[PDB]
Image (cartoon, coloured by chain):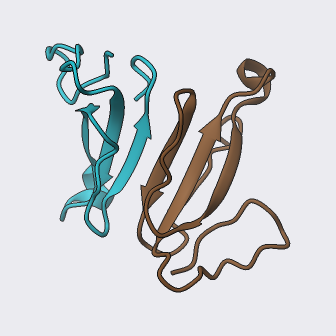
Chain colours: A cyan, B brown
């Protein structure tokens, strides 16, 4: 699997055991002014996230 | 918890113990033209979905959104 990542220079290749891509979004103190914080990666399973975090999971290449 | 729902006949109120709202999307035969199919609801945990189907989970009231079509 390949997934899009948080930084443009990162390898998109997932570790063997990670077939899900994800996009995690949340707000910080600057959320309304600068935008939502984001993290993109691979995972073995769709991440459980804290309250107030939003998580989008998919399992095709670069689907995030 | 309250969440957006797919059909007009569904109450927004979640069952007790279902604190997650979800947007589940996929493509049918018209996807490239008419965009994704969508289901919106409540759940106790974020639904696990098969390859080809995408799932977005959040845990605030009515947080489950769907962008139909082009920005307007």
Q: Residue at point 30% right, 69% down?
A: A51
Is residue A23 in view from this perspective? yes
Q: Residue at point 21% right, 59% down?
A: A30
Is residue A35 in view from this perspective? no
Q: Please determine whether, in this image, residue B40 is positioned above or below residue A4.
A: below
Query: The C terminus of chain B lies in which quarter of the figure?
Result: top right
Q: Residue at point 34% right, 44% down?
A: A46
A30 or A60, which lies in front?
A: A60
Q: Residue at point 31% right, 50% down?
A: A25
B68 or A54, which lies in front?
A: A54
What residue occupies the far bottom of the structure in this picture? B16
Q: Where residue B46 sits in the image (x, y, percent)?
A: 44, 57
Left or right: where does residue A13 sit relative to residue A3?
Answer: left
Q: Please determine whether, in this image, residue A44 is positioned above or below residue B56.
A: above
Q: Please determine whether, in this image, residue B58 is positioned above or below residue B16.
A: above
Left or right: where does residue A17 sit relative to residue B61?
Answer: left
Left or right: where does residue B44 sit relative to residue B72?
Answer: left
The answer to which quarter of the image holds residue B70 is top right
Q: Where residue B28 sits in the image (x, y, percent)?
A: 76, 27
Q: Where residue A12 sits in the image (x, y, percent)?
A: 23, 15
Q: Please determine whether, in this image, residue A6 is positioned above or below residue B22.
A: above
């Amino acid at each position: 699997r390949t997934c899009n990542k948080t930084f443009s220079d990162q390898s998109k290749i997932c570790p063997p055991g990670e077939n899900i891509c994800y996009t995690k979004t949340w707000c910080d103190a600057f959320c309304s002014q600068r935008g939502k914080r984001v993290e993109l990666g691979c995972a073995a399973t769709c991440p459980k996230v804290k309250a107030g975090v939003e998580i989008k999971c998919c399992s095709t290449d670069n689907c995030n």
